[PDB]
Image (spheres, coloured by chain):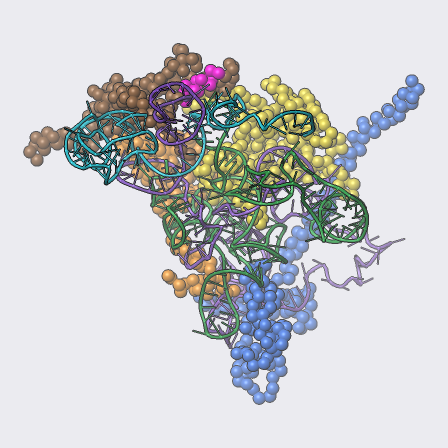
Chain colours: A orange, B yellow, C brown, D blue, E purple, F green, G cyan
Amino acid sequence: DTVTIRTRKFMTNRLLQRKQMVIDVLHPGKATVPKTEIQEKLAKMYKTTPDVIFVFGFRTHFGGGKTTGFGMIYDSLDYAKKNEPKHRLARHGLYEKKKTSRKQRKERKNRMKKVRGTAKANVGAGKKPKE
Amino acid sequence: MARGPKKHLKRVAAPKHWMLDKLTSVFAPRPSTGPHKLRECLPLIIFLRNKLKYALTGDEVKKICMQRFIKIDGKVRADITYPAGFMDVISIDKTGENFRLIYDTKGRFAVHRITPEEAKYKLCKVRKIFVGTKGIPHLVTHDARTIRYPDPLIKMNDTIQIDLETGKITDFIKFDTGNLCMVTGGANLGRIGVITNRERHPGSFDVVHVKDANGNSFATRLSNIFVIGKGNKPWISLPRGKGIRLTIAEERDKRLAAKQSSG
Amino acid sequence: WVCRKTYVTPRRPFEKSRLDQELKLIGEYGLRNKREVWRVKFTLAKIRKAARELLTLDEKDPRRLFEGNALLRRLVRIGVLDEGKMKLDYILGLKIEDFLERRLQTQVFKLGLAKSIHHARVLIRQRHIRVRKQVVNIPSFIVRLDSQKHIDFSLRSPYGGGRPGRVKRKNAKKGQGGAGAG
Amino acid sequence: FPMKQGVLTHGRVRLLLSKGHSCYRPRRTGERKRKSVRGCIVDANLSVLNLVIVKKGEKDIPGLTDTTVPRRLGPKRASRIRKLFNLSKEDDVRQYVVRKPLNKEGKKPRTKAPKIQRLVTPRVLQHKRRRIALKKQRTKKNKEEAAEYAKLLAKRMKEAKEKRQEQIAKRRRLSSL
RNA sequence: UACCUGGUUGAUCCUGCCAGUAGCAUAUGCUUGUCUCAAAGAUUAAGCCAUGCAUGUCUAAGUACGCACGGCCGGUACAGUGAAACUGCGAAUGGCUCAUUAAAUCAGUUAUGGUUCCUUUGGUCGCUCGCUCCUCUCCUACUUGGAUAACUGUGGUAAUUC
RNA sequence: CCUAUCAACUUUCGAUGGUAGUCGCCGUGCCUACCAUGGUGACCACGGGUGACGGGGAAUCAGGGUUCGAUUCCGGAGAGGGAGCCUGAGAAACGGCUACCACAUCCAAGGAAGGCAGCAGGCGCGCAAAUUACCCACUCCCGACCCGGGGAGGUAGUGACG
RNA sequence: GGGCAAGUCUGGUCGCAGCAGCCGCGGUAAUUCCAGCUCCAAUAGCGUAUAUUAAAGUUGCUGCAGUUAAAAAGCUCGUA
């Protein structure tokens, strides 16, 4: 309600091929209408199919009233997927990170040490221990 | 045990003229080795995402360097932290924007769009003129660009309009009295103006008495004096903060002005 | 990384004349404890000595002027000092209570829905007011000149205009369940 | 504990085994691991004697001479293929390479030959016309930049060296008056 | 905040310390509702350390003969991709800790015209200026030689990154 | 920093100077050949004492002054203690090695494999100190390198330090 | 109990138990106990321990004292 995305400091990021601006939305008494709404709202502002609009920010101002977000209207998803921090991909989930998680990969580094050749045997050397 | 040189560099114990923050990021960009000494140097990533702010994360700036959109000294850069020193143009190859690295009299790097006429040449006050082996004279400037066959009338501290397209030096400007010199370092950083005086001592430690454009006359050594051309003859544009000298009671009259006066 | 105390401790532990004098400023302005006395007491000793040192500086010093004219302006932007006097001799003559009047609490007691300075601290603490587009919850807020021109009902105070929380509803439930018999 | 080139006599010893001695499988640059090593000569102590029939006999061991354990990797160099036939090197490998039919490696067979190194191709002929291009370019670019200064040097002298004749004549006037 | 307060004595004036008196920063006694900040195995053990993990890395560009994967597309070496492996580089730094050292560290200032430096920035790469042409017969330039890893199997090994 | 209930010290072992060369990244009694008897102290040297890492800086005091710097920084020093080698530009590397010396493991008795003052965590000591946490995203780092890896670090936890 | 703010309370205790940094209570009509109550103090802190800084001009550089309270050598020359 009474949202009004105020694109402060608009930056035509030509070398990252995107529309880059600060999202500043207003509220009656409940801050932060949802992010993908703001994407879809910043879509129809720019007519840009908002699944290339990879937003973040969105902290709720005290007293409702306002929320500062941030917008990157990438001019393509290739313009998105070229720049794209993975936690912006995980800001609204359409790509996520590694879930080995992190200790088996550190364990596999202990496996290539022991024999020369056949990483499959060393992947297999890390495969049998699961403790 | 200092068993080799440090291959890491953290923040705030970092140069202040890079205008980094406090411990918000616990590591520094750490510029590479190259043409200039490391404190003179400026990382691209500070100029890219902390001065122009087209990026926000480091792996983008790696890919922006994989975009190869950055030409420093007219030469293709894929370094996020290239050791670029003084009067180094930066050609942002996608926005069509040239910026030459010069210092302010406030004490900050100037995001300074020179004309592309002024981007082909940069003025390097020379570092040495040496008769190399087999009887061959040379000039090598402060960015260590070893150039065979100098000019046959130049001497020390002459400024060469370094052709950034080629190297392979173009015309010079002789080290002359009263030249415009962006005085850099100490309490005289970023000050341009005529020379009007130089003092000599055998051994070391020669001071140079410089009277700038505002009338501040000051004796500051020739190490602080980088000649940028001819007296009352600039060769790029003047940076922000007038590039000469500013007083702080006037600076509040500056800082009150364009905030809430724009848009 | 860096922190500091915002209150102060005198070198005399029991100076009962002072101890009941500190009871006055709490009762005269609506304070929490003697810390709210000692908070402005922590500041005002530095303010007079900063006024003292700039007075003992030689004139036409920018560290006397540009710092001081800021310190002149900083004391006048909040409206505690007036710049019609505007010299270091009078800044030696300011007090605690000039700041206490420029707190948010007394200005609510001076202006608005406060009947008491018990009441005036409550209206900030129970967030009935907006000093800007700002639910402001700090009674020791010390205000500026423009700040005294936008203190309203909050839009989270459902009386005097606001979205209902659960209380005017409860006060409606005092007539719709307190009087509705269920 | 194995046997190597010079563990001399049969008694099991231990040597500071660096990279460059056998009976040793190294683990780090700059690491010299002293390990136990059994003597090059044989008393009785071994579990395995590594032996090689360099010349067979007349009645076959089935496991060694009737059995065949061949191997598959062929020459990835050019001239090994050529020399056995007394065949020349300007007249190339000229297919005899051991291309390896490797079936169901997708769903087809590949037939993969070792991509021969030390082999001049038309790409190498492109690069031989690219390498000493740059070397001959370097001799001329050295020669170009020399002649640019030499004209620039001598034309400056006609203002500089002419001052010498201006000072010899007034030297004799300064000796006069 | 430039302060003192109590205590000698029959009373008094001293000297004069005592003890009260505030700062602190750990240890702690007791108690604690929100919300912002956060020091924390230094003291004592620079003690031993269990365990978890703390420097990896392939570019269109070193070598694809992966037993791989994917294809007819194959031959001159051919694979799209590519584990490995050999090769290129870091691994010295980082973190941690201050035991140590009393002009020693360190700090400020200087100098290497005594010294060495990966990397990067820039020049330098036809030649023997022809042995007064082996470099025209020295005829290997369309390119050299052999020699290993991965691969394989034989394996031995209480145990081993054997 | 402390000490004269430390007044003289330094070389038989070069202590100090030269010359000469050796060697070392190189200056150098570096080193010896050789020569000289130097060199230096009451201005407290020489020596001994200091949890003496030092400093950037820190707390307090009207001022004058007084206490701190293991401690988010800089520089130094060690990774159990020494020694010796190695690698590379840079390491006597203890997340190298070699051996020793003091510790710790498997042992099937042959041998094999080990040093958290890395993150933690553990015990130990104490008055006294938290995850055996999560993530390589942020920060950076190394690479052949955008790619990756990282207990660096980030992240929260612990957490009336404050 | 004073210093030290606020109990010449109420009860008990009776030089006991305790308290009390110090000065001090308690030996029966306890303002020092032990409690009640009341009050004061600060306050999500407050109190203790130890440490150190001031107060302390009791280390006195500013700026100590040396006839009799501490402190002019037995006296003189006399170098640093």
Q: Quadrant of residue B35?
A: top right
Residue found at x 57% / y 32%: B101
Residue B37 image point, x, y percent:
61, 38
C55 magenta-colored: yes
The residue furthest top is C84
B122 to B132, vertically: above or below: above
Residue E61 image point, x, y percent:
57, 54
Residue found at x 44% / y 62%: A123
Residue found at x 53% / y 69%: D100
Total count of labels: 0
> Horizontal placement of A91 versus F150: left or right?
left
Along the line of sight, the residue nearer the viewer: F64 or D134 = F64
Which residues are the magenta region? Answer: C46-56
Q: Quadrant of residue E50?
A: bottom left
Along the line of sight, the residue nearer the viewer: B249 or G3 = G3
Residue B114 visible in image: no
Residue B17 image point, x, y percent:
53, 32
- Judged by its main secondary structure, the magenta piece is helix
C179 magenta-colored: no
Q: Quadrant of residue E148?
A: bottom right
Along the line of sight, the residue nearer the viewer: B151 or C71 = C71
The residue furthest bottom is D59
